[PDB]
Amino acid sequence: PVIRAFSQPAFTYVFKFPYPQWKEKEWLLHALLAHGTEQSMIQLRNCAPHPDEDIIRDDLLISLEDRHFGAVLCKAVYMATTTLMSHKQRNMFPRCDIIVQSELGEKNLHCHIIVGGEGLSKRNAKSSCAQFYGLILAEIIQRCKSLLATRPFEPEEADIFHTLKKAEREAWGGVTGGNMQILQYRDRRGDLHAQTVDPLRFFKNYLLPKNRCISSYSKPDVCTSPDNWFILAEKTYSHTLINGLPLPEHYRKNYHATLDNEVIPG
């Protein structure tokens, strides 16, 4: 079911997970965000990249499919975005379009959010950064607590948790630390614009053609199936939500092809 329409005006944000040591200490996030997957993540390190046969790899990935930490982060941000639009529209069931994609970057663990609909505008989109940041943090923090049903926090895990809560407090005071930003561009004359003129084309051209990687300790050629490999792609994605529904790894390249050929060429 390829998306064919996107509510305007639309805006694009980048959320940075506010923990600098996240690559070095990623297993902490496995536990805080994706409790139940921590062993699967470890086993994944030992997997052979495609096109080598590796059945363990294939099952492991099937069992991880909507549950790995990047996927959870991505659902958290989506829920927060829903909550955001809910506030902007004073309506429990807001009319909006939302795409969210999490990415394990070279440096940052981030999510891109494209959101559009009534209640956002040029007038409020940039200024809503701190509020949006706080709502996102509230969801993450809540998810962290689910681990507590199984065991108390280990010390390093508790450090991250309090880092989040502090960030959340600062967000309520309008500080984001640069971890929540709106994407802006210039027209010819050099004026700034925060509105994403073409959300689908930005999705199709910048977010879609990436290979998957679900861990700093794994590789894209492990996490991406051969039919979905983008030969010139240098960056990766972890998980993608389109209006609440995941774009499954095995349909990504075809999904892109359909957008590029039938729906929105160029």
Image (cartoon, rainbow, N blue to C red):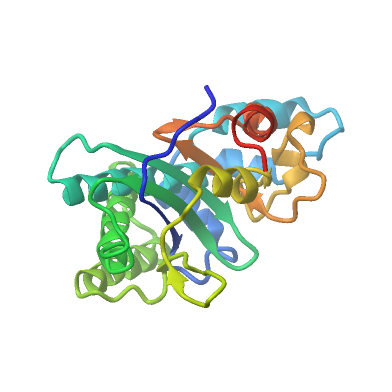
Give the residue displayed 24% in from the left and 63% down from the top: 131
Residue placed farthest to the right in the image? 52
Q: Nearer the viewer, residue 45 or 180?
A: 180
Give the residue displayed 59% in from the left and 38% down from the top: 40
Residue placed farthest to the front in the image? 189
**As drawn, 169 above or below 248:** below
Number of disc labels: 0
> Toward which corner of the image does residue 254 lie, by quadrant?
top right
**As drawn, 135 above or below 83:** below
Give the residue displayed 43% in from the left and 67% down from the top: 193
Q: Nearer the viewer, residue 86 or 7?
A: 7
Q: Position of residue 8 (x, y in %)?
A: 36, 46
Q: Position of residue 137 (x, y in %)?
A: 31, 58
Residue placed farthest to the top in the image? 1
Quadrant placement of the C terminus:
top right
Describe residue 90's horizontal placement relative to residue 101 as left or right. left
Q: Position of residue 260 (x, y in %)?
A: 67, 35
**As drawn, 178 above or below 117:** below
Q: Nearer the viewer, residue 227 or 201?
A: 201
Q: Is residue 37 visible?
A: no
Describe residue 126's horizontal placement relative to residue 94 as left or right. right
Give the residue displayed 42% in from the left and 38% down from the top: 6
Q: Is residue 172 visible?
A: yes
Q: Position of residue 34 (x, y in %)?
A: 45, 43
> Toward which corner of the image does residue 192 lie, by quadrant?
bottom left
Describe residue 82's horizontal placement relative to residue 109 as left or right. left
